[PDB]
Amino acid sequence: ASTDYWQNWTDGGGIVNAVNGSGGNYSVNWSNTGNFVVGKGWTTGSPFRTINYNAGVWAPNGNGYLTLYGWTRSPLIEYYVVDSWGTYRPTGTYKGTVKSDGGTYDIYTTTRYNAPSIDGDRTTFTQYWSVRQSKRPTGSNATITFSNHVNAWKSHGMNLGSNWAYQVMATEGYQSSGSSNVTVW
Figure 1 (cartoon, rainbow, N blue to C red):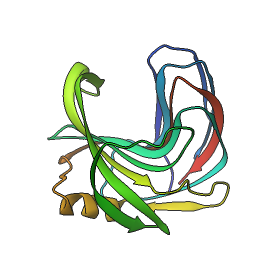
Figure 2 (cartoon, rainbow, N blue to C red; figure 1 turned 120 degrees about the vertical axis):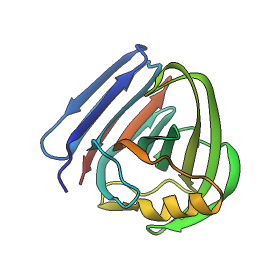
Figure 3 (spheres, helix red, strand yellow; figure 1 turned 60 degrees about the vertical axis):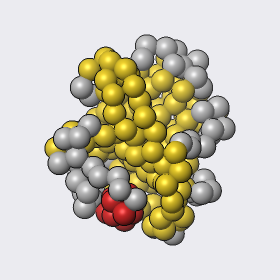
């Protein structure tokens, strides 16, 4: 599928050189950062979307995530399907596991409180996570069948909102440097 959304946000720390390339492709080179999130995808997310990607380069030096990323409202939820990472594998309140797309993922929730979100500088919300149990191979075509995550989350009582914001295949980092190159469809 064609992508129609470009995500490029930083808290102002370090230097993030995020380039919105042709088609579904983008690249990121970053250094000495705070927190930042970059990615390509869709303006309106869906719990039925299959996200395809090929990360030709996935070279975090320190803490970075290669992850599906998006939000809902009603209620406000930030969510992740983390396929790979750098030195830090994200975890939180442990819920259970789900199998999808040849991997096994642990399911977590975490709470942000007086934190920045799509709703403002100081807001409260839950984050929903699927985090692969081992770093996914990169450089070949990969699929995230998002519905399998949505359904597993629902079984553990984690309900997404009915108002869908953007939905992207993202590079996130925190206090790190690195590079990535990812094509999304």
